[PDB]
Length: 5
Length: 5
Length: 299
Length: 299
Image (cartoon, rainbow over all chains, first blue to last red; front, side, top):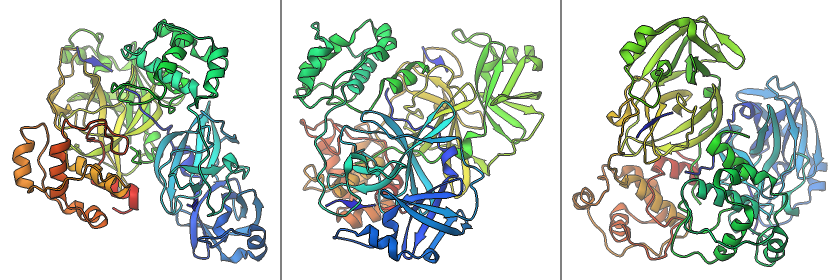
């Protein structure tokens, strides 16, 4: 997955 | 050989 | 040697603010009476898609606390702009610089001011890849960190950090809210697109090597820009454009682009055990501008 | 990955000035009503040895032109302090930060604000080698560029650029005028002394590799610090002092120093196409502080 910072 | 800047 | 350097960050440091919504806190860009920050500050998700239209409709202005240093800025209104929020605040940023918005192109370099809790923590140079991703260094709390370039007294804001892909690379939006590379500000499975070496930057690099006495790898052959370009597109490299920008570097080395293109073809994904300025492969990192600026101090 | 980052430069940027004497122009550090700069600005020769005591006696204050931006500063007086000049001017730098003078020790990292013609052009992080030299990026005009660290609101000035040795590496003086490594303020033939890998920084690096999934090189053996130290001194590496600073990194990897030390002896001058975090060699660049700060945001 993509990780929202 | 060492150059002053 | 050849360093990735950052431009001085002072002009941008005073535009950074802490944006807290409920529990969540990240960084915002504070220009005029407006604060730009990633919209996901009002959403709380870990594994599922976010309905941003709904999150915006439930949004409560009194749940915001925005601060510059220990100075709090009263929130007036908020609107959604792509992957960002426009937050109107109580006062003007007196230290607002002369600035513009500019969307970066692949191959172009800019600066990142890594911020945490509304304070600038580190600054370093990066380069936008054909991916429309960058190889930044970000951890938790870094979102809203601005990307910028200083051009003749003008600050060009080009990036607000949003996202880290599974490969470790990073994605932001421009200041209009548009996510680079059409990536989505969601915690969904998003595979980093295929990318090509930006050949013009590689050319700049090889010029830098010639300038620093690295000439073992030079080919005696040549290919025209027009035929290299048709090879490049099928070998994971970008096309070469005007080549006029390589005049200064060519003049300093007596080596033309065509011959460098030939060296590239023999080199690409087939280096020996040798290195070039401490590099084991062709690097995409440095532009002609950066190389010329760093070796001779002219622009 | 692992990036060399600089701390934000804004606090230092407004202390930079242009110091022109005769036809020589470089950068000065403009704090309070005093400007610090390299003494060789008053010399008439740059390629032949300089008699600085004679140069000081011939000095004329009206031949000075000192400027902050396009604002010129009248020179009041000048005294010689090691490899520096103390220059008194007609006004305080209103933007003078809270600062101190500090001399760097080998292995320690700090920031360089590369300056040209009295203006900051770039900022990057460097590490003081056992040589008491640094691998900076400087070209003509860079002399007087400051080195600094920002520690709890306080700017610790530790470096003013003076010299590039034939090897390409750089030497400056501290703000007390003392040349690092006892190097000389002259254009004489000066070979860069031997230097050793700062083992503590190497440990930090290998820890960073463990954290990001690089474990192929991990050795099965272990050695005591003091038995490693007796090997290190004969293999171009520094001794390891107290390993407490490695507690956080050890806790997160479950690997102690003794095992990293053993792996270093087998990785010293021996790799085999292998590469750790993009390095073909052991790097000296990153301290434990930087590694912990960059991965976890703790000090």
